[PDB]
Length: 16
Length: 196
Ligand SMILES: [Cl-]
Ligand SMILES: [Cl-]
Ligand SMILES: [Cl-]
Ligand SMILES: [Mg+2]
Image: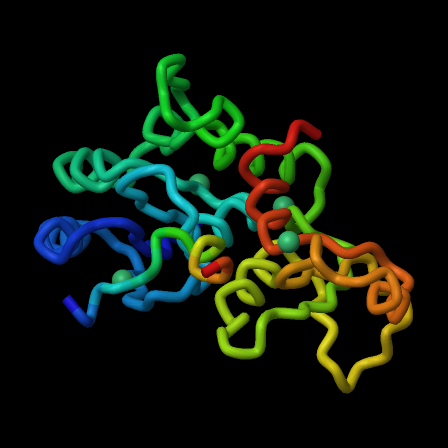
């Protein structure tokens, strides 16, 4: 759901 | 003694069931993707969400969903100890013993030393790739009581330069800063993996 979409890995998100 | 609750890692239906149980207890629940200074983070699993890393950096309680289920059934917030991520270590696991124990390690270490956060006295310049937001990284750093130096603030006393592609940058470019360069991953490793 769009209202429940926090990242489970913010380090990975910044690497790629 | 306050109970400011956030949750990380639960799908919508699981989260609905848990928030319904919070109505049986005096507490605050903060709905946000961001870390919002919860006293108790309920985590579905060990992870690297903003909430999980920030809660570690501030030495908060990071607990299993059973903490909510059992407290609601009892009509009263229970002792957190046996519900903590880190209370029991799985020797056969994809997660290292350090990462499995990280919430307990930081909670106990900050109480021992008196420091308010895992990054207290750090003064950090972030050089994050210009196409992505550094906002989650900043909120984790600030949860750990690091001072994130904005471009308009003086660079006096910088302790860390945390940089996208730090391992690629030229020495000439690193020479624009007195402090050493660290990759983005250092932040997660310092909290979850490094043996101090
Ligand atoms: Cl407590
Ligand atoms: Cl939420
Ligand atoms: Cl790097
Ligand atoms: Mg303290």
